[PDB]
Image 1 (cartoon, rainbow over the protein chains, first blue to last red):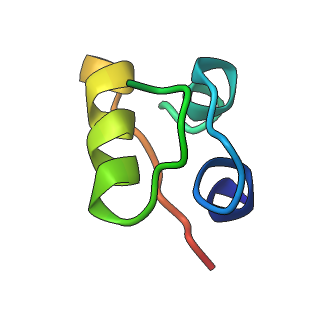
Image 2: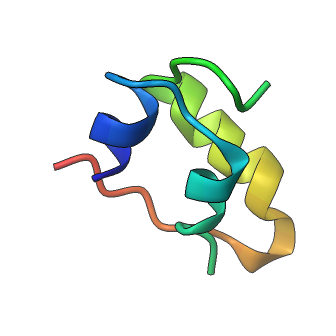
Length: 21
Length: 29
């Protein structure tokens, strides 16, 4: 999930936007 | 600011800034 993608690995705008409403 | 390791409050802040009025869901577990 988001922690595995953005915290324990390097985040990306692409990924963050997957979590927007 | 988004292309780095972002944990805890730093991740929430990035979601806030990116998503704007769309809002977001933060599910760490």
